[PDB]
Image: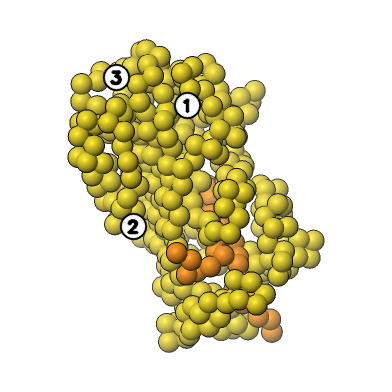
């Protein structure tokens, strides 16, 4: 049993499995950052 | 070919955006910017043209302009294919001053290769041209991008626009009854309270990267899309970012292995960022498009057009049911 906790800055890469496009790329440094 | 370049371009853009604003959220669509700039290159010749193609990370000793445009035509067709599982659409358009005549070859290529329909617009009525472009993007993004164009110089001759809309459901959705306010640590000693979603007892692709001191997991959407999540250890974000590349991404994917996970915690959040890409395009070698030496003659037949500004806005919503993400890119062009 392991735990993955995204409670500090992380990266998100949204991709098409087939065409291998990166649709979006993100760094979340603060989910509430204005 | 196009796949490798578009990924290379993605990570090059990411690194430059982080440099400009080290403390900010980042969210952008690489495919939207690549397609918008490739659309622009349809109208370019000589140094202006070769700078764009190489800035997009294509190797012109192994590819040609026609093959690059065909790659983007095929990509747009593949992305806009029907799906019962995922909403995904990409559109292109050109907003052209009413009294301006364009090459038939450009207008025809823009339609056939990029699916672009021209829009006659009175750029001398700024607020009408502004709302006309913004309504097109707002409509394409289902209301998510409302103010892509903030200011329009009155002497603008043309604006090329790309938008992307993405709305998908998680393969393994979160239960909102399990969503609880929890800490998100901006630093080792500072936090903000956010709604923290959670999943319990699940098997997902997983890879602990000890070389880079980060953990990678993959969450699937229904349909052909997925998301790589990378969690650097504390004080290791900059070290991971420096290692982002097509090879690192390939290594992570090839190292992923299904693994049972007791608990997964992911914030529910919505973020947006708006960008002036002039600086970054300059750093990639795309310069002549912006100067009096600009060669956009393949648009009207004369070297009388120059890019003034390239802008990008993107929005990412992450929630229990899935993800909604949207972006648009605009290339503003004035007489030379």
Q: Nearer the viewer, residue B320 or B287?
A: B287
The C terminus of chain A lies in which quarter of the figure? bottom left
Q: Of the two numbered discs 2 and 3 on the same chain, state the one appearing first in sequence.
A: 3
Which element type, helix, strand or loop, lies under badge 1?
A: helix
Relative height, residue B171 to residue B122 (above, below): below
Q: Do the dots labelled 2 and 1 sit on one chain? A: yes
CA separation, marks 1 and 3? 20 Å
Q: Mark 1 points at which residue?
A: B290
Q: Is residue B277 left or right of residue B207?
A: left
| Rendered residue at 42%/82% (across/down) | B176
Residue B328: x, y in percent? Answer: 39, 46
**Do the CB atoms of the residues marked 2 and 3 lie less than 8 Å apart?**
no
Question: Badge 1, how many Cα within 10 Å: few under 14, some, many 20+?
Answer: many
Which element type, helix, strand or loop, lies under badge 3?
A: loop
Q: Mark 3 points at which residue?
A: B102
Which element type, helix, strand or loop, lies under badge 2?
A: loop
Q: In this view, does B10 lie to the left or right of B109?
A: right
Q: Of the two numbered discs 1 and 3 on the same chain, state the one appearing first in sequence.
A: 3
Relative height, residue B103 to residue B63 (above, below): above
CA separation, marks 2 and 3? 32 Å
Relative height, residue B195 to residue B293 (above, below): below
| Rendered residue at 67%/48% (across/down) | B245
Q: Residue B103 carries which label?
A: none
Residue B256: x, y in percent? Answer: 68, 64
Residue B202: x, y in percent? Answer: 58, 79
Q: Mark 2 points at which residue?
A: B144
Q: Nearer the viewer, mark 2 or mark 1?
A: 1
Write down the colour of chain A.
Answer: orange
Write down the colour of chain B.
Answer: yellow
Q: Of the two numbered discs 2 and 1 on the same chain, state the one appearing first in sequence.
A: 2
| Rendered residue at 53%/50% (across/down) | A22
């Amino acid at each position: 049993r392991t735990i993955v906790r995204f409670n500090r800055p992380f990266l998100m890469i949204i991709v098409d499995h087939f065409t291998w496009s990166i649709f979006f790329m993100s760094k979340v440094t603060n989910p509430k950052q204005a | 070919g196009l796949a490798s370049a578009n990924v290379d371009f993605a990570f090059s853009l990411y690194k430059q955006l982080v440099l400009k604003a080290p403390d900010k959220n980042v969210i952008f669509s690489p495919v939207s910017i690549s397609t918008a700039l490739a659309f622009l290159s349809l109208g370019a010749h000589n140094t202006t043209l070769t700078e764009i193609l190489k800035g997009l990370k294509f190797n012109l000793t192994e590819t040609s302009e026609a093959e690059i445009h065909q790659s983007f035509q095929h990509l747009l067709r593949t992305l806009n294919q029907s799906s019962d599982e995922l909403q995904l659409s990409m559109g292109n358009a050109m907003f052209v001053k009413e009294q301006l005549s364009l090459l038939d070859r450009f207008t025809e290529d823009a339609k056939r290769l990029y699916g672009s329909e021209a829009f006659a617009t009175d750029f001398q009525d700024s607020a009408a041209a502004k709302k006309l472009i913004n309504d097109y993007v707002k409509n394409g993004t289902r209301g998510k991008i409302t103010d892509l164009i903030k200011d329009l110089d009155s002497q603008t001759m043309m604006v090329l626009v790309n938008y992307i809309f993405f709305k998908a459901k998680w393969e393994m959705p979160f239960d909102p009854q399990d969503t609880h306010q929890s800490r998100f640590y901006l630093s080792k000693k500072k936090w903000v309270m956010v709604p923290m979603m959670s999943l319990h007892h699940l098997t997902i692709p997983y890879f602990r990267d000890e070389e880079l001191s980060c953990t990678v997991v993959q969450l699937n959407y229904t349909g052909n899309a997925s998301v790589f999540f990378i969690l650097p250890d504390q004080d290791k974000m900059e070290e991971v970012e420096a290692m982002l590349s097509r090879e690192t991404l390939a290594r992570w994917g090839d190292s992923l292995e299904f693994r049972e996970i007791g608990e997964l915690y992911l914030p529910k959040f919505s973020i947006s960022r708006d960008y002036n890409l002039n600086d970054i395009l300059l750093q990639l070698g795309i310069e002549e498009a912006f100067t009096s030496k600009a060669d956009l003659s393949g648009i009207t037949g004369a070297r009388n057009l120059a890019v003034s500004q390239v802008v990008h806005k993107a929005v990412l919503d992450v929630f229990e049911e899935g993800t909604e993400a949207s972006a648009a890119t605009a290339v503003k062009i004035t007489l030379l």
